Picture (cartoon, rainbow, N blue to C red):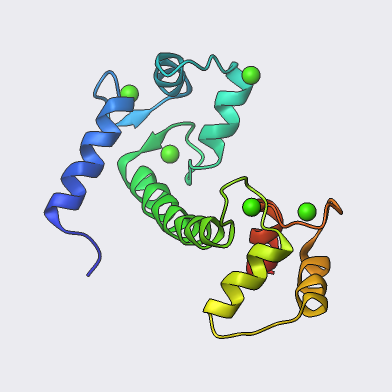
Length: 146
Ligand SMILES: [Ca+2]
Ligand SMILES: [Ca+2]
Ligand SMILES: [Ca+2]
Ligand SMILES: [Ca+2]
Ligand SMILES: [Ca+2]
């Protein structure tokens, strides 16, 4: 077990958007066509680095198996990032992108933890990198995964 016929069909449809000429491979040129359509104009060197990250056999192009492997893993990545984003936006009660001590304390009380200002201040100091006494999303992620 691994993938349904419907999952493979949608991966194949995604691959086809890149594989302009239908030869079963994605070249640097084709990847460039797609990004250019999206508003980015990478150089050949930048495109090569992108292919090199996903071209497992080193033949210079990305085939469908290589694209399935990298995509399926990107979607695990994305599912874990979404979980940290949702957790953050809850802590960040006013939506300003900074969890304050007051916000952290309120949400911790709802999570069943009645903490003092000093306790909360220590939690933030542990995670605070830029020294503003607040936790931004990078600081939050960094702490949560490490
Ligand atoms: Ca092609
Ligand atoms: Ca560039
Ligand atoms: Ca390859
Ligand atoms: Ca806030
Ligand atoms: Ca901070």
